[PDB]
Amino acid sequence: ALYEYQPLQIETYGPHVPELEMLGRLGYLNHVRAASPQDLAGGYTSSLACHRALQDAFSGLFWQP
Amino acid sequence: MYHNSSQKRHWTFSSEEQLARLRADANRKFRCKAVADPVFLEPHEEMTLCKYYEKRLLEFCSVFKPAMPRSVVGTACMYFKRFYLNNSVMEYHPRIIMLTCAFLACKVDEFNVSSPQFVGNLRESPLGQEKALEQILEYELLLIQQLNFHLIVHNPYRPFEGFLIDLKTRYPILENPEILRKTADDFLNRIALTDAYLLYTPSQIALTAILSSASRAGITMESYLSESLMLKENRTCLSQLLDIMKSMRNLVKKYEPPRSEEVAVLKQKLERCHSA
Amino acid sequence: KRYEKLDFLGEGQFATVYKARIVAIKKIKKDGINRTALREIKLLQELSHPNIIGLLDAFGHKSNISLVFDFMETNLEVIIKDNSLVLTPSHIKAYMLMTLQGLEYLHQHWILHRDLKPNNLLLDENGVLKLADFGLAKSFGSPQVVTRWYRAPELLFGARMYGVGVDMWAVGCILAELLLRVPFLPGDSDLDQLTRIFETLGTPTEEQWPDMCSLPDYVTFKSFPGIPLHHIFSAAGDDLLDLIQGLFLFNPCARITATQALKMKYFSNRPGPTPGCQLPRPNC
Ligand SMILES: *[C@H](CC(=O)Nc1ccc(C(=O)Nc2cccc(Nc3ncc(Cl)c(-c4c[nH]c5ccccc45)n3)c2)cc1)CN(C)C
């Protein structure tokens, strides 16, 4: 029984969030703080912060109790 | 994340009527326990006292040293609101519960503060500070158990920042989305006073604050909802969102701050209740 | 209380765990309730995945708190240290698959485990692997951790801000331990761990890590050629060697994430991962 990758299916009840690799091409990174060389050395990029902020802004926007 | 959080699952309610029912049930339960009288305060008086002590908690966290992150203050306020949904001020004193809420919020939000420097922010004698610390340590487990062990609180500040980033990126019509920050922050502060945190999602609250600031600035961004957010495909979703924003604005506009004379009378009544 | 002590499961870094009636209870050690237990509760009350341990209950008195989890039969360290157990490539594939799925679910919710080791990978009698010991787990994304043997080189250089790479390096170390049945890089100090890493894999240059010197606790090492990967793992296939190479990249940005590793050809190749009901079980 071979394995086939299947992406995680989690409903967010909000607008679609652009992909992390596409944030730079779409101009999102122009409005976040640029990561310092030390942050890049440790593996931290501004794309992560922008993606998290965008995910938080859209989560549960179309949901009612 | 919020879309599978315990805040959405267990601490977001349909309407203010359910909140009033829960508060009345708590008051009635404490009255029944006491029986098993004019001194008892009514649920609306309990609400007035809770609002006054929430303001006291806000000004306590405002002058906290070292500087307290705003997320910690929001977490403490949410803890206070959740605790007094199913508890009466006539059983647990809100003066100590606010301090326990601030203590637990500082612990949960990874804001490292030791107990001596926490109690040093109180305008009390060292003996009074030690007594307050002992009360906080006694009530910490009670606060945790009354929260159903749901300590992660989602605040509208991160969704607000994300919405601002999206407006700066995909909405050239709004030339400078940074001019709406102050009024949106004021609207968020006014939202925090009402029961909006227990009835709406943080993203909805942030969007409501942003569009309230835009309306007060004379800017209309119905295209941002319809076009940028792809709501022109789903019209009923747009109508529901607009109705949610209108309900939030109505909640904000009808809130009445507590009055000093009533606050003093209720404080005397609460002191009489707790002494006896 | 409602629980009766049965056995003694061991001592953690911050608590004493025992088997009770089946569940497992951690007894956490003027500051109030311990921050590690609060962190574990606040993080495990927000996650729901088959490969993540679920917090069942919590109680205590005043500033003493006790946590109750579902009881797991064993952990991966007992599996590895057992000399009577044969770790076939299918078993290794299944263990890595469960670990990577759990870590992908954890990372999508912006949480780093930061304490990953074979003893923290719990196994039940049904063969399901779970991640536990979230007392050091932290949320990341908003602008001196992990055990030394499984600590990433960027952590050993005093990195303050990091991402999923610190978990993926530990995952690579666990994979190497599964392959060799012994700890891959068993150092006794941070400098010794860095020396062992550079001897086994080679000293990285400015092309494999474009910001080596930016880290505060960074020191210059001798240039080691590095042992070839197929020399270290003689039985590893080409796809497994590619997965190991991706897992052990010195650049934390270039290091493969959990989703990227799950998409790799190693997991989709043959044979398929062993089902949990057929995974090796330590004999009594
Ligand atoms: C005969 C048959 C038999 O079953 N023998 C046997 C073999 C192996 C083990 C074993 O290793 N058990 C074990 C070790 C460690 C941990 C656990 N489970 C567990 N579950 C929940 C939690 Cl939260 C933890 C945990 C988290 N952090 C921790 C730190 C330290 C210790 C635990 C811990 N662990 C199971 C047992 C039995 C047996 N009889 C005679 C028939």
Image: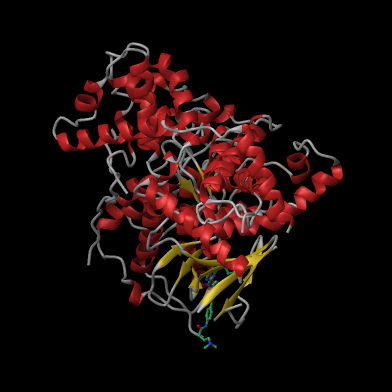
For the N terminus of chain B, the quadrant is: top left
Question: In this image, B261 relative to C284: left or right?
Answer: right
* The quarter of the displayed image where residue B50 is located: top right
* The quarter of the displayed image where residue C97 is located: bottom left
Colour mapping: secondary structure
Viewer-proximal residue, B97 or C72?
A: B97
Whether residue C134 is visible, yes or no, is: no
Viewer-proximal residue, C200 or B246?
A: B246
Q: How many marks?
A: 0
Viewer-proximal residue, C133 or B163?
A: B163
For the C terminus of chain B, the quadrant is: bottom right
Viewer-proximal residue, C70 or B180?
A: B180
Question: In this image, B171 relative to B191: left or right?
Answer: left
Q: Could you tell me residue B263's position as x and y percent? A: 63, 38
Q: Could you tell me residue B5's position as x and y percent? A: 41, 50
Residue occupying the far left of the picture: B233
Residue occupying the far bottom of the picture: C284
Q: Could you tell me residue C125's position as x and y percent? A: 42, 77
- Ligand 1 shows up in the quarter that is bottom right
Q: Residue at x 36, y 32 (%)?
A: B250
Whether residue C141 is visible, yes or no, is: yes
* The quarter of the displayed image where residue B170 is located: top left
Q: Could you tell me residue A58's position as x and y percent? A: 33, 36
